[PDB]
Amino acid sequence: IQKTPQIQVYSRHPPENGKPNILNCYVTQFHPPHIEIQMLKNGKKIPKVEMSDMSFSKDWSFYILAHTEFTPTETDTYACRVKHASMAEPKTVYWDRD
Amino acid sequence: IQKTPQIQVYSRHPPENGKPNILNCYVTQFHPPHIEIQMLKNGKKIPKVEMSDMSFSKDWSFYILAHTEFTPTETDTYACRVKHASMAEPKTVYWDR
Amino acid sequence: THTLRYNVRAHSLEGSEKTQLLVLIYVDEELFLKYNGDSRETEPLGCWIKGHGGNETCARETNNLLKVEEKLRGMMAEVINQKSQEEGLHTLQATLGCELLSNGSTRGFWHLGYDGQNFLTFDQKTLTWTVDGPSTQQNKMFWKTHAPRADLVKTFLDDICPAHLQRYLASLRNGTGPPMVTVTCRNYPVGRVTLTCRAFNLYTREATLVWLQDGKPVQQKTFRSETILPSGDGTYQARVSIRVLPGQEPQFSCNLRHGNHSIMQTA
Amino acid sequence: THTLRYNVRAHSLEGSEKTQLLVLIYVDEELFLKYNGDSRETEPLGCWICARETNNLLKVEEKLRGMMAEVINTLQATLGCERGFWHLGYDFLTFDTLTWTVQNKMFWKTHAPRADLVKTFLDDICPAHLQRYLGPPMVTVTCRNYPVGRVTLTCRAFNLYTREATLVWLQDGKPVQQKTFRSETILPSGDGTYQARVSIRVLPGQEPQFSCNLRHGNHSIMQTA
């Protein structure tokens, strides 16, 4: 039976505007093992997005890490949009630096 | 100077017995472009076999896709047989699963 | 980023006028147009495109293709004439075109192949032809002068081809389904089980399949334009097999990556 | 608290029909080393983090193969450390008292691996293997005047070598909130290392009293707001 994916978006290293970095989209606890992941910059699709192998967790669920190279600025927004059969609509989670 | 063909035989869709499908015979990486391709059902030539244009890749070697309609069964065997100047005898590749 | 590629081949080297050509046009690695001047062909023209007004588009662009074949013949006339003098049966090929970069600029290319080997290459920076194989200085100079004129080459690659690509991309915009994976098992060979993972319904020629044992890759294959399998209906498929011991099947999962999709199926 | 586990299966090599062991080595329950002598298009030596290890791997394969020569002559076995264990079978046999616990008894007891060589492997040689197999983290704190009436403090720990970590919020040295990170709550950074995060809301003006403490392995690292 289906489980809804949890989505977390975060930088690989401590973020600094103008410094090259990696933005991660960590997608966990979903089922069935079919996911669709898109990463967005200012609402527009990022062409080169890397995905790890899908993994199985002990709680009978799957997870995967997507990421893309980026150079953060003050005004650029980043987001991860995810499609999965447990969700009627795609789910978007914006990068929040804090 | 002469390049031996690679021969791959595979269904267009996931095969199920009794359900209409298409059998592909994908012949690649050969030179010179002149080649003879036959598809076989139970050892005998299948009359209506379609073939793509013969194109070529970055290293100039040629490829062509041959295909035919077929309905997979438990007992019927299928093969692709290819003749090219690079080989002494016709090469035959049987379909599996 | 987008690519327009012309794959040209002479059927038999007679002369610059009588030599018949096969021209295949690829947009983003997908066959789009064909002209085959082979006298024995009942359908000399071909056009692969979907959507409304597709038939009108084919009428226009196959007619445009006829003009391209004329230009290509003209530019390559002297190479064709010189190779037509060779004894026996030989194969002349060309690949050429342009690449639209995401920053709006254009990269052109033009290569010739002879008897399945690199022959000539047009140097974009230098604007001269490079002889690719081992060659005397005499033969280098010879081909540098009989190869397609540099000013004609550059206009075609820098101006004409990019305009064509742009026109093609517009007609293509009128763009389904997700990829799928199957896993089959066979008791073969003797003391083994062959696990076969197949991915179907790939929309492009890019995909990766990996066999995983306890989360760890044991076999991995990346499929590209020239290694992925055409399914024949305009979609693509791929395949990776491994051999394991009887009873081990539950330990192994196949993971497909294609576009934005990641799909896993356990054996 | 640390587990070495060998999973082995007899099999024949395609060319010469002699028997080897396909061995899988699990340190702490994750696949670590693999030797498959009859690989074809896959790698015979597998390792995920070496070359020094794979060299020893070949040696432990023969050692294990030799010890089980009699019962090898579909045999599978699982053995390892931490207390040792060793089970056999064609899946039934267990190294309990220095004897093997199952006409069936007569056959298994005779062919079973020698209890002397087995005890030594489990007591000394295997722990050594497990022993053989077995920069600092950094902590950042950021603050935001948000939400209204509050300041939000966020503590992030980077460069964790393992997936275990504790982050503590302290106020003038007094623990206020705490979170211990597991698997499925720790965050992969994507470069082999892991990271974690805790946040807290305080009154405006409380910020200078607050500090974040990371406990990871033998690291105890402080960072103030």
Image (cartoon, coloured by chain):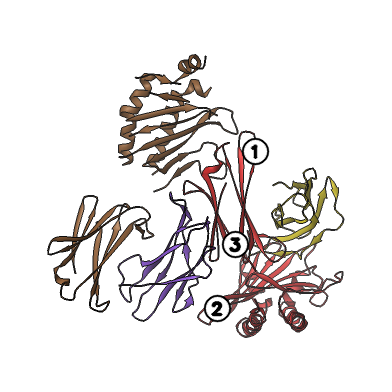
Chain colours: A purple, B yellow, C red, D brown
Measured from the top left, where is residue C166 in percent x and y?
Answer: 62, 83
Graded by Cα atoms within 10 Å as few (under 14), some (14 to 19) or many (20 or more), the crowding at tag 3 reads some
Q: Residue at the location (69% across, 77% down)?
A: C146
Q: Secondary structure at mark 2?
A: loop
Q: Secondary structure at mark 3?
A: loop
Q: Chain of mark 2?
A: C
Residue C35: name its quadrant. Answer: bottom right
The amino acid type of the residue labelled 2 equals Thr
User: Label 1, label 2: how many angstroms apart (C-alpha)?
Assistant: 59 Å
Q: Assign the C terminus of chain A to one quadrant of the image.
A: bottom left
Residue at numbered disc 1: C187
The amino acid type of the residue labelled 1 equals Asn
Q: Chain of mark 3?
A: C
Mark 3 or mark 2, earlier in chain: 2
Residue at numbered disc 2: C126
Residue at numbered disc 3: C224
Mark 1 or mark 2, earlier in chain: 2
Measured from the top left, where is residue C174 in percent x and y?
Answer: 66, 79
Residue D55: name its quadrant. Answer: top left
Q: Secondary structure at mark 1?
A: loop
Q: Residue at the location (83% across, 75% down)?
A: C18
Mark 3 or mark 1, earlier in chain: 1
The amino acid type of the residue labelled 3 equals Arg
Residue C220 in view (yes/no): no
Relative horizontal placement of residue D18, taking residue B50 as reference (left or right)? left
User: Label 3, label 2: how many angstroms apart (C-alpha)?
Assistant: 31 Å
Q: Chain of mark 1?
A: C
Residue C25 in view (yes/no): yes
Q: Nearer the viewer, residue C203 or B86?
A: C203
